[PDB]
Amino acid sequence: GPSFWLGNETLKVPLALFALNRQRLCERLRKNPAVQAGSIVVLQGGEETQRYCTDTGVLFRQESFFHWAFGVTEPGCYGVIDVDTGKSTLFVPRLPASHATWMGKIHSKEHFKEKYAVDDVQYVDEIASVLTSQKPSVLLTLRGVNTDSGSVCREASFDGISKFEVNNTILHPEIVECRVFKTDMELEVLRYTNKISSEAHREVMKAVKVGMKEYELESLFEHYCYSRGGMRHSSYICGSGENSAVLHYAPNDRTIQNGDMCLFDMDGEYYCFASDITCSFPANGKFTADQKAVYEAVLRSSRAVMGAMKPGVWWPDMHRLADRIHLEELAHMGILSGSVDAMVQAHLGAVFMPHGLGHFLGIDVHDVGGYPEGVERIDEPGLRSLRTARHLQPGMVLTVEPGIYFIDHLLDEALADPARASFLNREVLQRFRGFGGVRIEEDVVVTDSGIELLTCVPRTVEEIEACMAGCDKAFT
Amino acid sequence: GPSFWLGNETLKVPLALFALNRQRLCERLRKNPAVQAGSIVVLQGGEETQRYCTDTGVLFRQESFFHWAFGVTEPGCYGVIDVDTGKSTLFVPRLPASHATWMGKIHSKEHFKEKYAVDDVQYVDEIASVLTSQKPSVLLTLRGVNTDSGSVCREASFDGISKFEVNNTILHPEIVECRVFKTDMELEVLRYTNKISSEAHREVMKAVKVGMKEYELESLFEHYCYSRGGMRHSSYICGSGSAVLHYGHAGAPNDRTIQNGDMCLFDMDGEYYCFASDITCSFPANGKFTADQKAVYEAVLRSSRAVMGAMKPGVWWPDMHRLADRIHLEELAHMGILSGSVDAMVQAHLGAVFMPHGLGHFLGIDVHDVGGYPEGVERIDEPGLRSLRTARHLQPGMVLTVEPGIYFIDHLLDEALADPARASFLNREVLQRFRGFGGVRIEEDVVVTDSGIELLTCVPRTVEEIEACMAGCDKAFTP
Ligand code: PRO
Ligand code: PRO
Ligand SMILES: [Mn+2]
Ligand SMILES: [Mn+2]
Ligand code: NA
Ligand code: NA
């Protein structure tokens, strides 16, 4: 069958991937006792947008649920799926002849049917008539709350939809749940995005020089991923010095200084499939003793979490595991003193890692389904920032991204709190003010017995220093 | 005073640039008989947006009028200008403490005042109180129609604005007219964006190889402009012999393989600190012009240079478009593609078959800049000319693109061959050879001076210059 491809060495993605997703969605809806026979899923694709009142185009990127179901790159489409039969119909714009002059050839409906391997193709201005002739019981539209943005998914609408019975509650939790579990075809794409991104991160480590601007590295990274991978930046983090303390840190215009710890967090996507990797490393290519200690603490928690991950593991337990390891290591360094058990009970870990350990990844970098009905957010420091509190199951894709930061306002808050202040050694901590931070982010897939690591970048102090010194890769 | 700067070799842009724009706007409004004493200009800046219902951020880019007046890069601001005194007040978001953790340092209001060289800074949630205490007569807000998009400009609004008298008609044409005429400080930025982009175009010509994907050149171009210039792609064109055909939108990767014998047409735009550039280079994929390629290319070079040589204050822009048409038709006849009277070809609008777009457009903070069709200036309802983005007379301070081209577009050629009024001009036996040629476009950015133009762009343009550039010759080499 047909595939998406940007030539050269880029990945061929079979359109069969999206056919399988439609099948899986129907199979799930059929088991839902509230779903009526004769229901049709109706999804509306994204449209081209312009900046404010200008004719300046914003780069078009397909809406994620619609992409998941159909893999369609063109703006202005709809897609429907007959739940009982699984039959797919794509609706495309009826374009005018002037489109031939400055946009391009006007493809036939046949062309799109073959391109996307759907059962039928019709024009958008005919959607109400086509759906009417199919005599559906109910139209299932998409509406629900994204638990990272807090935004409400926008329901499909078309001229004449008011004449149909519409249900906007059933679909969202079901299609979200399908997205949580990646198919083998989906995993192939995520392996690819991780491969390209990993290569780009290596090139960044090889290229960094004291005196460069952060955005020079962003530029190189993006150039590698686009020219070699057919990939683009996903969500709009190259922090050197105390900017590495800033989690989501426009062009990053800080000059990389000698002695800085760089924290390079980029994401990217191929055909709307994401990757999210973070590398930390000394700007000048040589870890100081302090940098090595902080860095190896995060390497330890990173590897402890990956090693412990398997089906049945509760994700908040992994977050707490990283906290405990960080506190142990900060104590070994002399930054902390006292009982680590007591430190954990006082939530001291969150002073140094205020964000969640990691998140679902897929078509969105912060992928859907972290907090389905019945799964609650934990109202404690650190944990409340987790983007899921679910138990792990095979097929889930997660980032594992512990970090340690020295953030003045969190440190000062702890120092003012008698329940936490006694753990902190001001005279040692003073040395780490302005250190910035370290974050190590891997992408992994949960397997039947553990995980599969998708990411492949230098991680040990030795590996990183060798990479940055320009040593041939084969060098040990 | 303070400046915007991205370090290294990038341009330092004084915030005085924006102060001058505010002063110029106030000076214009003070001369406007309908403007009430005590009026204040109220502009609302852009806000951060996310992809659909996700938390995936869209790259923030400031709204153009707001940028023109204030140069503010932060989302969620407002800006006001007292017309009678010129006093400026920037309103910035009151950020929560968690911002220190996730975004960066929470800057003071004094920090922003110093950064932007405005007279006062307040928090956005205090705008109604602050304006009430200043007792303005009228709030002048922004509403009007962009004549390229057809969209209506979004008026500023804030909770409590209903308690003020608001006029939304006066401001738009006046601030548009200010933007049409670039200051000396604005021209320095446009010279810079043209310099970086010109350098990037040279690198593309130097790097291109048969067998590459078009998007590989786009990537290289964008990397040069960003890493060396601090610039970003502006509006979402690397055509050989594909992005819209294969994926449905220009922003998609152009994934056509560049073939031996292809004519490349490389049209990119970009911006530095929201100031645009828009340049197009055409060149043979394999670095050697064929006779046919030389002939078509030199035809467009002739019209480019004829228009640039003719441009000066008082010239009617549509006359320049017609001049380019006539030259294209003359040269296509000299090639044997056309035959007969060029006077007759023009009367039959044959030029639009080969150049269906406008000769060029205003450029500034937007690539297709504002003010091309103010009230009283009409769009010409003829092929080609109806696509012009302005029908104004040229005056000093305007910045325009000059981008004639010749294309071989099957459905336009076929229409002409089926039209008895046009068909007899075309020689099918020669034209058939140019089916699939693609096209040539040569786009320069220029400033209208007191007596002519200043060319902003600096790329190889003659056949010899282009072949030398593609052969890896130093810039300073002149063949
Ligand atoms: O947003 C998140 O959850 C992670 C934390 C560090 C940056 N990205
Ligand atoms: O849109 C315009 O006016 C010009 C014509 C060719 C591409 N850009
Ligand atoms: Mn992440
Ligand atoms: Mn242009
Ligand atoms: Na991350
Ligand atoms: Na152009």
Image (cartoon, coloured by chain):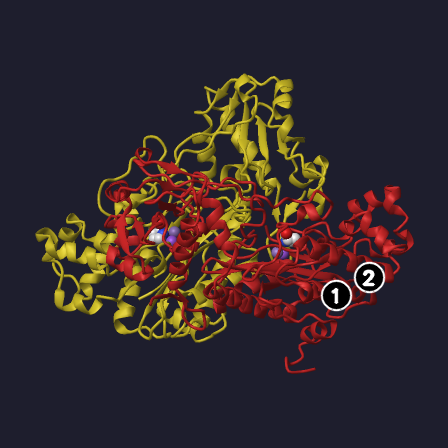
Chain colours: A red, B yellow
| Spot occupied by residue A340 in the image (x, y as percentages of width and height) | 85, 55
The disc label shown at residue A300, or none: 1
| Image-quadrant location for residue A117 | bottom left
- Counting residues from the start of the chain, the first of labels 1 and 2 encountered is 1
| Spot occupied by residue B286 in the image (x, y as percentages of width and height) | 36, 75
| Image-quadrant location for residue B429 | bottom left
Task: Please tell me whether mark 1 sits on a helix, a strand or a loop.
Answer: helix
Q: Quick check: B398 above or below B217?
A: above
**Residue at horizontal 70%, vertical 35%?**
B109
Q: Which residue is mark 2?
A: A329
Kindly tell me whether residue B235 is visible in this rendering: no
Residue type, label 2: Glu
Disc 2 sits on a residue from what chain?
A
Total numbered labels placed on residues in the image = 2
Q: Could you say which is closer to the camera, residue B416 or residue A151?
A: A151
Residue type, label 1: Arg
Label 1 to label 2: alpha-carbon separation: 9 Å
**Residue at horizontal 36%, vertical 70%?**
B257
Q: Could you say which is closer to the camera, residue A274 or residue B314?
A: A274
**Residue at horizontal 59%, vertical 28%?**
B86
Is disc 1 in contact with disc 2, using a CB cutoff of under 8 Å?
yes
Screen quadrant of the C terminus of chain B: bottom left
Circle 1 residues within 10 Å: few <14, some 14–19, many ≥20 = some
| Spot occupied by residue A295 in the image (x, y as percentages of width and height) | 76, 64
Task: Please tell me whether mark 2 sits on a helix, a strand or a loop.
Answer: helix
